[PDB]
Image 1 (cartoon, protein in one colour):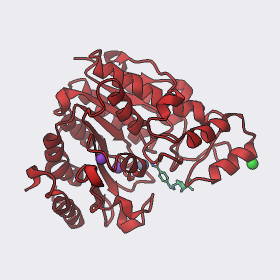
Image 2 (cartoon, helix red, strand yellow):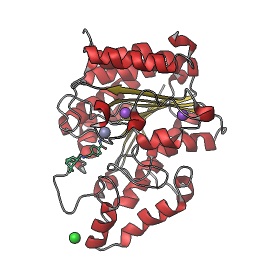
Image 3 (cartoon, protein in one colour):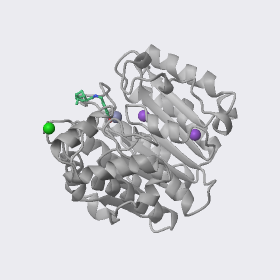
Length: 353
Ligand SMILES: CC1(C)[C@@H]2CC[C@@H](CNCc3ccc(C(=O)NO)cc3)[C@H]1C2
Ligand SMILES: [Cl-]
Ligand SMILES: [K+]
Ligand SMILES: [K+]
Ligand SMILES: [Zn+2]
């Protein structure tokens, strides 16, 4: 009956030495943590310590070469950090980046351990840099290692290889790295909702479309819900949960739920362009709590309006703690999107028929 929370100020040390106004700001996590104190949520949680991921733990999802390259950045002079960052899509690197990425992952491992050992029922991880764009072999989109993917594998590593993990990715961007890491996996169901715009929206790949349903044994275990045609909000996200996320998740019967919880679909976010409310995120969290006997871990991904993300993630933690959720026609293109995913996944999920 207990909610865990992990936060460590040391993850603020990752920074952009060339553009101090880059939106993936150190203050993202400190503003969220402060808001939890202001709302008297922090004192209601069980504090879970951060730790470093080990390199062996990173090898659950990443190549030895990728690990060694990111690790080599901690001793680089600035022009070599610039060159290295430029070898990726939308990455900046400081000497502290690698350690911060390790702390983000190890924090999530400790939270998953706390859940799976029964110390807490659910947990929230206020971490940066984010993870879901990171691939096996490369960094991408502000992400170095795929924290959520690694946490799924870590969870399997302390229970059984086939532990059913559901990852719900409600960051406004597609988690390309998460999709690829689990594309052939039927033990990890990946469900992403994301702005798509026929490939115009970052990370700009048709991999994010609704017809990418997984490969081989994982066919049916990758659910992309792509939005086209501009701003979406609470109605569209509630309908996507109602028609797709929750029926599929209930059929899958996960033993652990991880939320890749970006808050860049929030009202006010300058990169997402969407209008999901803090109350909306509260309802999404409360629905996911009905899964997996409540074993839910909310992991911060993106989200760039400091006030928006502080309010939205605090609302999610309020739901984890058992507070009552707070108090409509869809954009026509959202109906088109939902029906496209429904047709793509009806062959795999009887609940959609
Ligand atoms: C040059 C810039 C720094 C300007 C200000 C934001 C970025 C956005 N370019 C791509 C992008 C978006 C979002 C994420 C993300 O991880 N969101 O969670 C990752 C990558 C470019 C434009
Ligand atoms: Cl330079
Ligand atoms: K997403
Ligand atoms: K999968
Ligand atoms: Zn994002």
